[PDB]
Amino acid sequence: AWITLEKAYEDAETVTGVINGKVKGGFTVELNGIRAFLPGSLVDVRPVRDTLHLEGKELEFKVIKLDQKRNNVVVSRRAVIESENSAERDQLLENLQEGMEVKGIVKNLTDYGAFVDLGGVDGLLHITDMAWKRVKHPSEIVNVGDEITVKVLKFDRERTRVSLGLKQLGEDPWVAIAKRYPEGTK
């Protein structure tokens, strides 16, 4: 099995595997007795809110990384997912959508930011920038699969990543404070 997964890493082979469980960062797959990890942002082209149907199904994965030292292989639904996303990443790379303003669907929420799919690029929408308010948890404002319009603060071309912000639609209250609250106000 270990020789099998190493060749499929070299040969880019499609291997059948069973997803044994889902964790906060992805799904656990088993391939010929070797433990695989499917990243949450890499599970499917559609951010299907009902992930329960993905548990226990035999599905094919492409070996991205084989770790001899840890007995774990990181797989994603590759082959199929990589050529389409390169064209779409290039399209977003060429369009840049008036400073990357785009409707996006939140694939997964993390405690330091939200993963928002803009159709090819991964954005971290930080809890600080989800709203002007210092929210303790992103889960109350945006649910997995909600469409939010977010404005990009930073575009990382080399990693095909965008840093997102929601604050910029809400008129900056600090500039209003300069007009609302002079020094000395109780």
Image (cartoon, grey):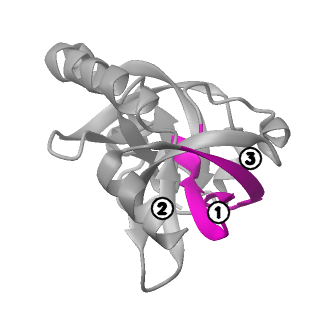
Relative placement, left or right, of 103 versus 94 is right
In contact (CB < 8 Å): disc 1 and disc 3: no
Check the image and report above or below for 114 versus 119: below
Q: Residues within 10 Å of mark 2 (few under 14, many from 20)?
A: some
- Quadrant for the C terminus, please: bottom right
Q: Which mark is residue 32?
A: 1
Q: Residue at x 26, y 15 (%)?
A: 97
Query: Residue at image x 50%, y 53%?
Result: 75
- Extent of the magenta region: 15-43
Q: How many neighbours does mark 1 have within 10 angstroms: few (below 14), some (14-19), or many (20 or more)?
A: some
User: Dot 1 lies on which element?
Assistant: loop
Q: How many marks?
A: 3
**Picture coordinates of residue 91, whole percent (x, y):** 23, 15
Residue 42: assigned label: none
Label 1 is placed on what type of residue? Asn
Residue 94: in magenta span: no
Q: Which mark is residue 4?
A: 2
**Which type of secondary structure does the marked residue at label 2 adopt?**
helix
Q: Is residue 5 visible?
A: yes
| Chief secondary structure of the magenta portion | strand
Amino acid at the residue labelled 3: Glu
Q: Which amino acid lies under the numbered mark 2 shown in the image of this protein?
A: Thr
Residue 143 point in image, percent of width and height: 71, 38
Q: Give residue 39's position: percent from left, percent from top.
A: 54, 53
Q: CA distance from mark 2 to mark 3?
A: 44 Å
